[PDB]
Length: 167
Ligand SMILES: O=c1ccc2ccc(O)cc2o1
Image 1: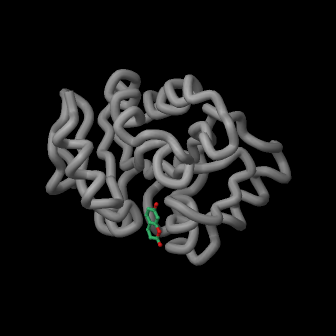
Image 2 (image 1 turned 30 degrees about the vertical axis):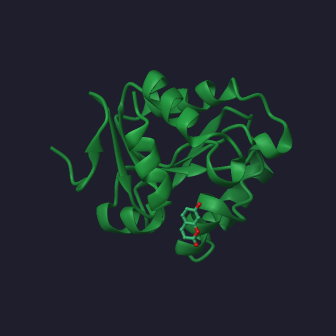
Image 3 (image 1 turned 180 degrees about the vertical axis):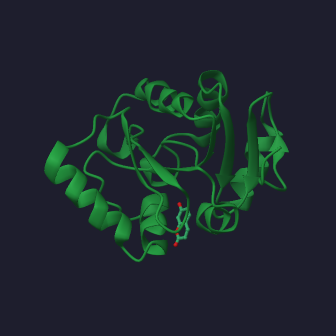
C-alpha cells in the first residue's frame, strides 16, 4: 500500500490522475518525483519551471552546481538530485524535445530511467512544451516502465482524452 490517492489504474503498474504535479508532490512527499528536464538542467518553464519555483529556486542552484561539475546530461538520460521540499529525490529525466528536432525514439530510453526506482510520481515525458504527442508518450510509458508510476496530467481536457483513448 502507498499514499497516492484518486488515481485511475491503467495497467498492473501505471496509474494516472488529473493533477498539478507540484501540488501532488507537496501532498504525498513521494520518494521520487520526476522532472521534465533539459540537458542543461535549466528549469525555465513547463513542469521544470513549476517544480523549481516551488523549491524557491533551490532546485536550480543545486542543478547549476551539478552541471558545473559533470557537464550536460544526454537526451534520454537522467540524474538523481535532491527533491527539496517536494520529495526525497528528484529524478531529472531528459525526454526528446520535438521543438528542437530530437529523435522521438529517444523517448523509450528516457522512460527506461524510471525502472531504476520502485515507485515514482511523474509527468508524461516529452509532453507539453517538449512538443510530443502525449497519447504516444503514455503508450511508450506503459510499454517501457515496469516499476510503479503515478502520472500527473496537468490539463483536465488532456487527461480525459488520454483515458478515453487508452488501449
Ligand atoms: O505554474 C505552473 C504550475 C504547475 C505546472 C505543471 C505542469 C506544467 O506543464 C506547467 C506548470 O506551470
